[PDB]
Amino acid sequence: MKVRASVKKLCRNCKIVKRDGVIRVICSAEPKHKQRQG
Amino acid sequence: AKKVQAYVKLQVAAGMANPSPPVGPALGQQGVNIMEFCKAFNAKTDSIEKGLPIPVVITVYADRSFTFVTKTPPAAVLLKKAAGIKSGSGKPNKDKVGKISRAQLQEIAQTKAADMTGADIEAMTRSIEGTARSMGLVVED
Amino acid sequence: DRMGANFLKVVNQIKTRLGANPVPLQLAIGAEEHFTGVVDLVKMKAINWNDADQGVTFEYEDIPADMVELANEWHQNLIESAAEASEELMEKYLGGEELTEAEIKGALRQRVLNNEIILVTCGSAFKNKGVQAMLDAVIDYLPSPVDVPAINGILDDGKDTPAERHASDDEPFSALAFKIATDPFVGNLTFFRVYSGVVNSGDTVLNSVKAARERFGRIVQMHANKREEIKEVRAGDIAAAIGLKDVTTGDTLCDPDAPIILERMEFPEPVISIAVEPKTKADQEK
Amino acid sequence: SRVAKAPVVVPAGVDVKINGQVITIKGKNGELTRTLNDAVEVKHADNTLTFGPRDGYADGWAQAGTARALLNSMVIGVTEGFTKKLQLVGVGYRAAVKGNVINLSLGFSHPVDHQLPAGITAECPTQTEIVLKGADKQVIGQVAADLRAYRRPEPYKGKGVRYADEVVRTKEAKKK
RNA sequence: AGCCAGGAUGUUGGCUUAGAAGCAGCCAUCAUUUAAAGAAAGCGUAAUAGCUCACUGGUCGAGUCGGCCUGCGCGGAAGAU
């Protein structure tokens, strides 16, 4: 999980759910599109 | 006719026996002997002077079967068969070269009227005027 | 002796990819780790191997009880393989004359001169499991230089008359030149094989395809590595036709006034080209 | 809501034991009980079960929205069951069932044989296909996902242990 | 929002045709049928077969959706007996 202050909804099918409070964004086929902070 | 299994209309000029690589996949969909589609159409291909893309459609069946529908060549290539060059659309609304009147357009529409139930005479007349303006062609009668 | 090593899969994979007709003979006993027996099906005997020794036992027993039915359904396909090899075994597959170990190989050996079936054997080289088994088929399923069509020297240019010469010692001499290695002792060496005839030591052996004269020096045999001087070369040995002045790929090694062979079929093409450059300017001289 | 427009119909062959907050479902082949939270108002009304969110816990529309989906699965899981098949694609990798134990031919220097708990009747038609049967929807995944986590789907070959319906995304080497 | 569900089909959409064949990119950017379809968004990809968006055409049978303004909240937030 890459970390950066900006979670920008980037991939076309990008889920966003708030697990534990810190946002981590869920793609389907792209592992590269998953950030976690912010 | 059929449904979500397979329906693509793709065939180009039938002087070439071997399926051209981009056409290949529409024959590479439901397991054909590619010699069968070469031996089906050549009984009637000897009634033409080859050079224009003639279209067929493919449609499939359960076990190993298939079917296909023969029509006439479309008027879009018939616009640029008489006009000499096969590709004229470089600038649509800035080129004024080449005239054919409506009388040529209906006699290449009777061969549509004797083949197909859509692509009717009077409705296609503006689109056979519409494929003229995109190519940069003129029309007067 | 590995995981995923199914014997019956691979021999029945040849009929799908290679499209051939293999009928295997020596089958498998053991779940690849407690593997102890190789199932020869003609004599219907399993062979015990070494506990872990580099080669003690050869103990033959019967078919074990854990494979009493797979030996049944596979032996009946072995004895099929002579009824459709020769036409004469067709009427005793169905009539029920006994298909012994010795009778079936007399048809199948003639099925190696046309090569429609290959003979397969499972086992281990490194675990010493099968190597002592694999040798007896070579004298009975691989062909001999006197059982094959022998040296067939055609002519030169006059007429196409292919002539089967004799495989015995009663012919003009004949050999071929291949695997022509080098050495810093004598220079050029060969790994040549003589098909029939006997040569003495010291001969005016020519190379009759390229019109050159050579003389036959001190011939040396190997254990693939060690110099052993073979003086008298008998018909069928493989040795080193030493001292050839010029020699090409596959020309004859033959006395004059004799038949002459001339063949260089399928001359290859080395494709990838890299340019070597010297280090010093004294190096490019060498 | 959609969940409030979703009542569940218990059929004959599965008995409920409504001691208020604790429901123990007496079913076909097991006992699928869940001790829910106090954000629910449960009533097996006539035959079709009706539920309700308790006051104070107005977020119990979520907490019983779990429950409406929950007990529907329980009455159909204790009777019919789940086929949870896994596909073993591994070089020399086998699967064989004995009692309640599964072998794991997993490319190691030692065998892994792990015993599997109750609510599991496992089977193996071959070395690469493995049945799991169960009554709870949780237990039919939890014992399945542990095996898959021992050898995840490798996206350079397609290697690994993977589900029947799961479709991996294998890549290409592209350098050497 | 999901299961059935056609992805109605003129066309090869040129150019330059080697494939730039709706899916590389610049100019057109009409539509034969319009209760469902654009000379077009990505993946499959040299091109396409596979899979969709397009209208949800038929079922559920009620609410639902994208942004503007504020009350506060979370992440951003790592230091040295």
Image: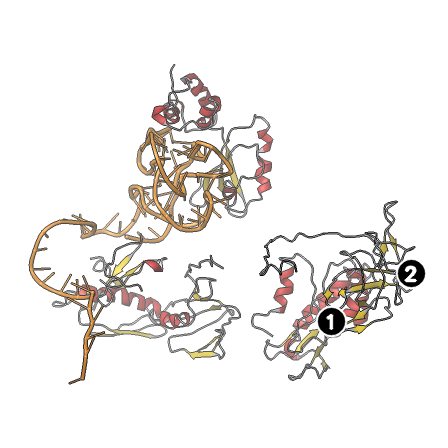
Q: Residue B60: percent from the left, percent from the top?
A: 49, 43
Circles 2 and 1 on the same chain: yes
Residue C9 x, y percent position in the rendering: 61, 65
Mark 1 belongs to which amino acid?
Ala
What's the CA distance linking mark 2 and mark 1? 29 Å
- The residue shown at (38%, 18%) is B139
Image quarter of the C terminus of chain B: top left
Check the residue under mark 2 and report the chain it is in. Answer: C
Check disc 2 and report its element: helix, strand or loop: loop
**Rendered image quadrant of residue C195:** bottom right
Label tally:
2
Which of C76 and D28 lies nearest the eye of the viewer? C76
Sequence-wise, the earlier of marks 2 and 1 is: 2
Give the quarter of the image for residue C132: bottom right
Percent x, y of residue D36: 22, 72
Residue C127 is left or right of residue C104, and the answer is: left
Q: Residue at x 31, y 66 (%)?
A: D73
Q: B141 left or right of B15?
A: left
The residue that disc 2 covers is C171
Q: Nearer the viewer, mark 2 or mark 1?
A: 1
On screen, residue C76 above or below B121? below
- Mark 2: few/some/many CA within 10 Å (<14, 14-19, 20+): some
Which kind of residue does numbered mark 2 sit on? Glu
Other-residue count near label 1 (Cα within 10 Å), few / some / many at <14 / 14–19 / ≥20: few
Instruction: Identify the residue under disc 1.
Output: C224
